[PDB]
Amino acid sequence: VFNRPILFDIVSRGSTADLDGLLPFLLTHKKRLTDEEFREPSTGKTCLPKALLNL
């Protein structure tokens, strides 16, 4: 349901409505926000730096 491009676009849009349900979906699949296949591959940027930059 939630992937890296979709989550990045959602957090860049600065709306805490489409990101609802990310926590249950992430915990059921036994994932983490810091997984390599979940963050930006070129640099290592995660959702929090993307939110701060797109403030």
Image (tube, rainbow, N blue to C red):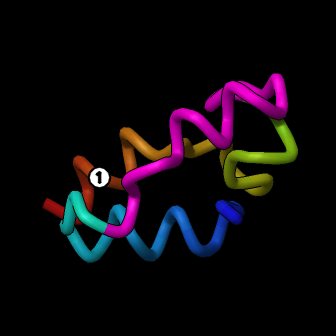
| Depth check, front residue: 10 or 53 | 10
- Chain part drawn in magenta: 18-34
Q: Quadrant of the C terminus?
A: bottom left
Place residue 9 in its image quadrant.
bottom left
Q: Give the amino acid at mark 1.
A: Ala
In this rendering, position of residue 33 left or right of residue 18: right
Q: Which residue is at a point 76% across and 56% down the rendered structure image?
A: 42
For residue 44, above or below residue 40: above
Q: Which residue is at a point 38% across and 53% down the rendered structure image?
A: 20
Q: Which residue is at a point 69% across and 54% down the rendered structure image?
A: 40
Helix, strand, or loop for circle 1? Answer: helix
For residue 9, above or below residue 22: below
Place residue 33 in its image quadrant.
top right
Q: Return the x and y of residue 44 as percentages of the image width and height.
A: 66, 41
Residue 27 in magenta stretch = yes
Q: Quadrant of the N terminus?
A: bottom right
In this rendering, position of residue 28 left or right of residue 26: right
Residue identified by numbered label 1:
51
Q: Which residue is at a point 52% across and 46% down the rendered structure image?
A: 22
